[PDB]
Each structure stands twice: as C-alpha cells, then as structure tokens.
Length: 184
RNA sequence: CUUUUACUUUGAAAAAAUUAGAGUGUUCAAAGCAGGCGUAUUGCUCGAAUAUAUUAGCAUGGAAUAAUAGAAUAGACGUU
Image 1: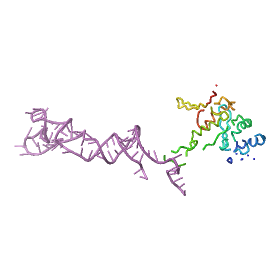
Image 2: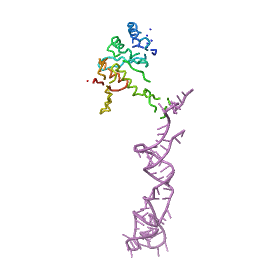
Image 3: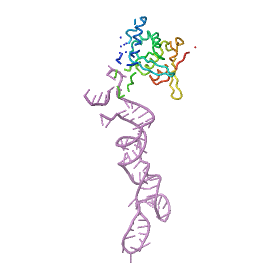
Image 4: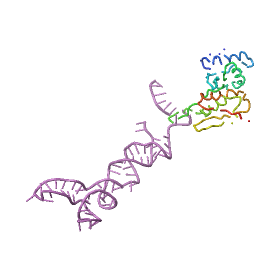
C-alpha cells in the first residue's frame, strides 16, 4: 500500500505507524470502510517523567473532523500495538510573527493565526474526548507562570493516566508549565 | 540620505555708566581709576579685573521626562 496514508516522502519510526494503519483496515473491515483516505505529516517522540513514552502525531489539518470520528477507537488499537506509548492528536498551525515598523502588507494576521489561539487549540487536542469544562492562571513570586486547566467530571478513564505525560508534551512544544483538576 | 519637537547642558555673541564686586589710605568716607618704589642728581615699575548681564535666536553634549513618526487593499532590506 504505506513511503503512503506517510504525506511528505521520508523515515524510520512513520512507516511502522503508515504499517499499523494499513493493518487495521486490513484486519478490521468494521474500521477501511472511514480510515481509507485519512492522510499524515510527521511524528515526534517526547519523553515523560516516570520512564514512560510519548507518541506524537501531527495532522495535515482538515480531518482533525476523520480523525476525531474514530480516535475513540483508533488509539486503544494503537496503545496495544505500541509499547509504554502515548498515542496523541494535534494541528500543524501556520503561528506567524507579529509585524514589527520597518515591517511588512503582508495581507493579515487572521487572529486565529496567533501564538495564543494556536496554544488554545493545542489544548482542545491534548485531551479531546473529555471536552474542556473552567481556564485558570497562576502567577507566583518568581514570574511563576502556570496553567490550572479546567476538567469534565465525565469520561476521564477516556484516558486519565497519560495526564504525569500530558503536562510534558505541552512543554518541549512550548516551554510552559501545565496541571489539571477533576472538580465534585 | 540623515523622523521631528519641547526640555537641559554648556559655549559663544553680546555697550559702558548703573548694580554686585578686587585691588588702592580721596586725611576717613561718599568717591575716584588711581598709585608704588629708587641712586627721590636725570629711572624702575605694579595695575586700571572678575562676575552678573535671564526674555527671543544660533552652535553645542545630553537622551530621562512629555509629545510625535514610521508597515495591516501592502512595506524593509538585494545578492538576482
């Protein structure tokens, strides 16, 4: 098939990932049916505190729909087909600098194309099935900076455990300090 | 080709008399621009200041304060 479902050209970790995708449409019917056209960019490993990895997907963009359609299954077959591993879903979003003064016009920025936006989206798609409820942020005497993130108290089992990892994955990408809370 | 301002530094350019002020015994002082010594038998000299003198304008170092300007139907450098 699979090099296909890679969306670049190169490639070491991806082709096993492509393989395990072209394996579920091979093995599971119900699963080809949705999965067949769902293309991706590249992957990035990222380490977490207690030994345990985390499997960093990056999305073309459009299907974030496609992908959300069958995530809450897809991951579960993948977490088994890869160990330790945390598989995630997030999009690659064309951030931009602010126009300086000697700068330029180009055309704009389209708000949602700004550092915080993207960082808000990075949110929605670090968790996903839970839905964000409530945000909160700290400011400590060493200008800390800490987001509390508020969660809904329903489906946090989809995955809890993750969590220890989540904090990290939102750290390499950004250089930040993230926490959660289950409210009662 | 080098946005612009105010503000501030200095510095000059600046009329003396006045005003402040150094000298100096008009006998003192108010003054004044004088006086001082010798071989006072025939020649020597010290000076006659500084400073204030603002408001406008120049030249000037400051770059805090307070304004203002560059680029959001697109500009900035350019090796092509």
